[PDB]
Amino acid sequence: ELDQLRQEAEQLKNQIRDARKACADATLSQITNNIDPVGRIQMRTRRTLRGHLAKIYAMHWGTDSRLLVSASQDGKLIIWDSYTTNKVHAIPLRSSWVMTCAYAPSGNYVACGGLDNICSIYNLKTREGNVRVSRELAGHTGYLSCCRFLDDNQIVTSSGDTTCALWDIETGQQTTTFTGHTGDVMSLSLAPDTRLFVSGACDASAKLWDVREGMCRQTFTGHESDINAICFFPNGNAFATGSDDATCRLFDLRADQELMTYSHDNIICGITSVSFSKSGRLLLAGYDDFNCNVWDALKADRAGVLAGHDNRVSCLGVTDDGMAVATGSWDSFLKIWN
Amino acid sequence: LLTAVVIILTIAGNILVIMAVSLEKKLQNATNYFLMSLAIADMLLGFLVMPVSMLTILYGYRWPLPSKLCAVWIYLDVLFSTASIMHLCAISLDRYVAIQNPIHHSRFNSRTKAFLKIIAVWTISVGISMPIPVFGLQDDSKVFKEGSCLLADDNFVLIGSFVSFFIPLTIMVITYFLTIKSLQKEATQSISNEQKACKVLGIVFFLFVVMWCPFFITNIMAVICNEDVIGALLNVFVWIGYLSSAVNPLVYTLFNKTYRSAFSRYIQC
Amino acid sequence: VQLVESGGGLVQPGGSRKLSCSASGFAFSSFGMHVRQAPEKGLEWVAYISSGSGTIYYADTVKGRFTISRDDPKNTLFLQMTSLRSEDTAMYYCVRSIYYYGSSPFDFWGQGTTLTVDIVMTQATSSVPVTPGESVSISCRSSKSLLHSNGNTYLYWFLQRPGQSPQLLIYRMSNLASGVPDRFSGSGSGTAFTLTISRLEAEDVGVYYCMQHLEYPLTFGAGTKLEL
Amino acid sequence: TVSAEDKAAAERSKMIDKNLREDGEKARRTLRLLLLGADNSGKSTIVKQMRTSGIFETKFQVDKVNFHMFDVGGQRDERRKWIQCFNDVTAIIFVVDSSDYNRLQEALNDFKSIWNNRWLRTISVILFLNKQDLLAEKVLAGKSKIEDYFPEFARYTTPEDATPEPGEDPRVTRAKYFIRKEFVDISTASGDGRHICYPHFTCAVDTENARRIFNDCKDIILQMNLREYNLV
Amino acid sequence: IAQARKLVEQLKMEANIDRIKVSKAAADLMAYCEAHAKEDPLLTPVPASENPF
Ligand SMILES: C[C@@H]1C=C(c2c[nH]c3ncccc23)C[NH2+]C1
């Protein structure tokens, strides 16, 4: 009985492979052959924000391109000001172990989550001038790995028990549960039109979900190990993935298959974070080799290096208007490159 | 000349340590910064004082410089020597405190004690050094001794020699005995590390105590008083002291593997 | 969030007095504190105390005989007055303010207690007859430019109802306060500022003031009275 | 070129910095430990005299020294992802059960995986052997045999140089020394020397267990101090 | 036990998806990346008068 099921599954998989192969006539590299290179770039650190006393685990640029929030291991979540390197708020957390934070699009909420399996929401703008906890969303069975705001009243969470959830803040209970993965879910990314998001887990497979129904639409497998970060192209029809094999990959949704890869021989370490530029011509990256790289999005030619840290880089971010790039690391310092 | 080789060696040895501390981040601890301060003092002494003595020996008990240009050379020579000796004593006391009880030493270490120690040792050196040139400039003729700049007043010589050397020496010997006994009591693969620590401590202490003592004993033997023999011996004992000052940092920084690899890389470059 | 005051009464010249302002309902140590009104004149600034007692300012008219202190565990502050004159009869208010990026200072005003014994800002209008259901506008002129290098024009609009304490309406010439209906609006350019009210109705009749906050001391306007 | 509001904001930032300095300075006085045991090991009954599904915490103080111990019971069988956080702790505590002979190989594989990890090349490990009285009862029972599971126990070298406990059955000493040597062999096979292991033996009802941890944390810190002064 | 039915149902639902040629996708990607060449402050340098840092 079950063997017949496995047989039809294998036949359908082979048919899918043939169907996805049939559409590949000419690759991306042979098309972009005649393009003037972007030349060479070099950026110098413009600022340095100090004040943390432990490792930094996450950050998130504000929507007004001036404010940002950072989360540390010592248990404090603090908000900075980029231009005048001041401090606006410092929030003491209940649990010291914190691995993810998110900053609301409206500008008056923040979210926090870690090993305690609870996502906590803090409200910023209120009377009496202190930050107080609004909600403590619980219902997961593994460590929270990522969280993102959809609207002012909706949040999506990716946990470490092979599942993702969509919540309603006021009600305080889940309304949709995405469960297709088989390994730990590590990364999550939304889309500009706010209708579908992508997820990446430890079983070396990325998935394209839908926010309304709750059904998987496409799955992509092209990696040899677990993936640690994911980004999404500004156009809305492509994305880039990074694993700990020192190989980044670019995938297209409509073609349903891989397009191009970025890799080299001198680098054999893992990748911790990726991000695209405003026009999409460049691709940032963060390695365990105590530095960062800059890849061309069309040619896979290393066109710059940013090295100012002594420990590994944990978080990377690009401003909405494309003016600066912020990088944090494990030496309690995060820097701004322009 | 052998003396010329010694002056070049002093500058070269100190310079490598300064490059190793600043260019490499793994060596950015406070203790290495204190050792860098010691290296800076040694480099100043070796770069400035010694060539003048070389020229004087080349002539022989004669000053090409004006007669009034004697107080500064003595003042600089004394200040740097005293600074080096107090640096060694402070290092020994710090090592004793660290080895005796590690948890409380880590509790009380805020990584800022280096600045306080540096200020304390430099101030203590300056306070001792100040008396001599002020009195010397008033009557240079009395201090001036046929081009030797031998200190005419025996009383200040005794007062400085007793305080500057013997008082640190007794503290150093007591603290060395205490560390050795504590490590032995702890012992009687960590045991091999403890044996290595005991060996290094003994080597360093014995090298220091054999390096400096004869000069400070012959200074007192001269003043307490054939005589020409003592006068000749002093000229060799001062050079022995300078050689010890040159040698000091290499022994301290040689044993660490990262230091050895950095030094080999610098020699290759 | 409430402020209460104790002190006052008839005082002979050459005496001394102490006024106490107590807060209840908010975090008192995070805020900075500040204002008096003559019987028939606009508001005038007096003195300022910072948070943590790290900065104090006084006005030139009141320099040398006035002291301000604060008790944080008790959540109170005191003003001590000595060597009074015959021109110091007024009513005194207790004001809070907090300063960070995007904040709204001067957002709350106390009740005020009566006691009986530089940039020049001018407001032209004194009394304007108005008709209900009609839009109105008010202007406020200035002597020197208030626009700063970074692009912020520091100017505040205050409304005072009859027999009440004033409340904030517009801060930094463009933004709106909390709980203020959207009918009010403000606009202008360098050394020219206007407040516009559309679909005007009842309960909005009072006295309006324009204040600058570019540098100390802080000078108010002459005021404007609305009549039916 | 600076308004008054900017000065007030700078004062606020400086006050926040002062508070952060004080709070961070206060926290360092305590020591940190991670307790992890496979199963059926009684890791809960290690220290019992002195004493949120994802994280469990236990605080105990000895000689004014404060120790925080973290035990995690809300995670899965695979622990390769949430262990990067614990790379700044003082020492890891490992607890096994020697009474049961069926699951010793699993414990050895777990210990080998932990010892040869990539982010734990500087963290030394304290090892406990729990439930020794059951071991004694089982070995004097004479039913279970070791040669069936471990073939090298049949031919063993007498531990004459090592000092056995004063008064004991030689068979018990032989078996327990073989078991301990089994773990020490895995510990020393790499032979790197950056970190070392401290084996111990523990009974079911033992009142003193914080003293053993204290006089081992002291040795760990002493080794670090000896290393960073260039004496080794 | 019966999870294979769910897996095969999901695979069958995912089987019928329309696809496009790679060349057209690459052409669209290059068009999008070329339309905003002058709007990228990082790709093209900016004078210090306009740079707020
Ligand atoms: C002649 C020069 C003097 C030296 C000296 C160091 N400390 C002293 N304390 C008292 C008297 C002399 C010295 C060493 N270098 C040679």
Image (tube, coloured by chain):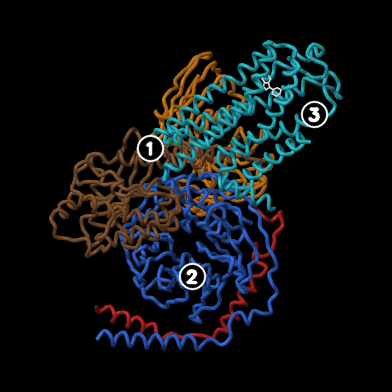
Rendered-image quadrant of the N terminus of chain C: top left
Disc 2 within 8 angstroms of ligand 1 (CB)? no
Foreground mark, 3 or 2, reads 3
Tell which of A242 and B263 is nearer to you: B263
Q: For marks 1 and 2, give the CA distance.
A: 43 Å
Of labels 1 and 2, the one closer to you:
2
Kindly identify which residue carries mark 2: A193
Marks 3 and 2 sit apart, C-alpha to C-alpha, by 80 Å
Residue C25's tag is: 1
Tell which tag, 3 or 1, sits nearer the viewer: 3
Colour in which the image shows chain D: brown
Q: How many neighbours does mark 2 have within 10 angstroms: few (below 14), some (14-19), or many (20 or more)?
A: few
Q: Relative to A101, is D211 above or below?
A: above
Q: Residue A71, image x and y in percent?
A: 46, 51
Q: Colour of chain C?
A: orange
On screen, residue B170 versus residue B6, left or right, reads left
